[PDB]
Image (cartoon, rainbow over all chains, first blue to last red; front, side, top):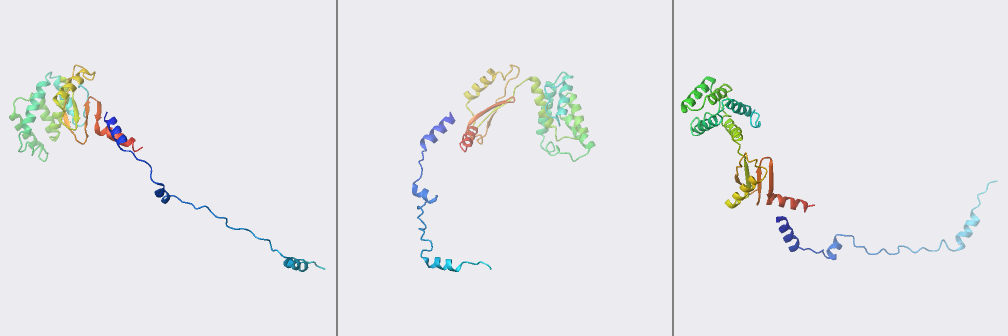
Length: 62
Length: 187
């Protein structure tokens, strides 16, 4: 009765629809896709080090 | 045995008055005469208001009682014994209280149902009559007790109506419905 009237009038006559994405963007974390951080490189290329290590390292006792 | 005990403090006095006047047989006479002296106590404004408040002696109280029985020589003797009781208990601050209570017991003995139809505004006389009819039609009226319909104005009870009588009420006020609607629509 009064319930119905209140229900009918309020519900019918008051309609909402969700807010714009732009406003939403403000309230959320936006995200710009992560890049590739690093491209690895050759592992100590050149026998300069290698020759040094082969000759230098021995450390054997008598 | 009274027509259902109600009221402890002061109402043991009322109960006693009732049952004693049941043994007097004349309860209506007692009540009517009490009503008349009570009314002239209220319509005595100097000291019939300003000496309803104990501050004076037992002996002085007794002499006030003596003045009261000069004011009416019709008061039965049981309600004159009631005057004795109240003077002896030196409690005058519950004289009209006892009067009201005796009225409740008395009109219970007479058998008159009591009720009220509180609303936001005074209702139509057609509404009053329809409600009076309805209440008599309802099993609530035992045909032995005849409702009082008292309209009360209570805007705080926003719209609707609430019917009350016995320990049974139907509350179809607007305020309660709004309250519930809102509350559940906060859920």
